[PDB]
Length: 71
Ligand SMILES: [Zn+2]
Image (cartoon, rainbow, N blue to C red; front, side, top):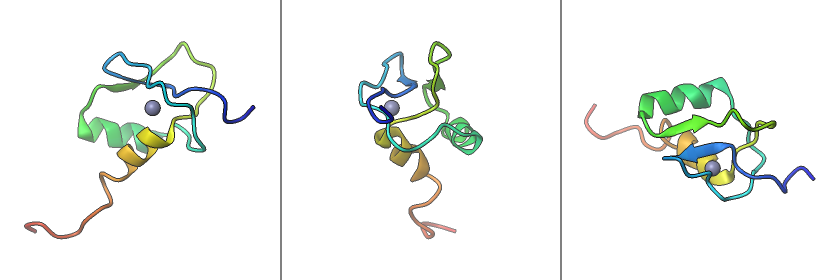
């Protein structure tokens, strides 16, 4: 019902394949993606806003993982 859907992101034209999780597609995530500059854009043919755990973790853990490397 609320967990039997699929991801609404396309990784290089690939409709993920992994089902949707508890996360939601927001602005912060969009901005996060833009910074990373990758081939991940929202699909407009969809009706819901729910991404998979895979993309959620992948996108969230790029601006929060370490705090020391060179500066
Ligand atoms: Zn996905």
